[PDB]
Length: 134
Image (cartoon, rainbow, N blue to C red; front, side, top):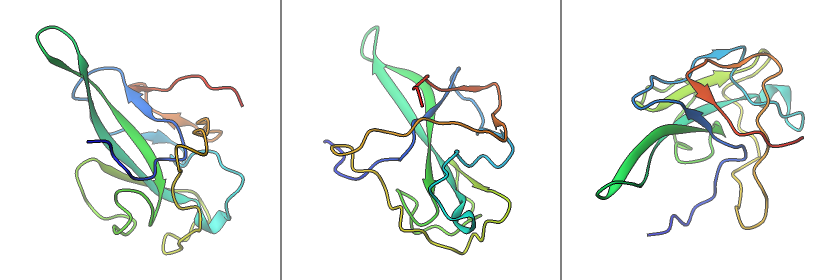
């Protein structure tokens, strides 16, 4: 089966080892994105367990986490702060986490993913992401 849905606007962050806890962030944990209302600077990171072929059959690879603005993505029906394994919530100063933006999600056939930057910090050392130029 091929997932039919829309995707995250940003690249993934990726754990370096198996069974890593959720990412902790210096600063808001909200990706750099100047094209949003300050009131709308809030969302969640969502865990994605990965695999790939290796010896015998399939082989576990470290988790990826993907960021979605509140009210969008797989956990669109969740409200900011709602507890669920594999969901961590982030908000920048001045955010109103009741607000809902028009950003929606990314259609992969049309737009490439945005590069991740965190001018106010970034995730802890259990995590890394690929370089994509600005």
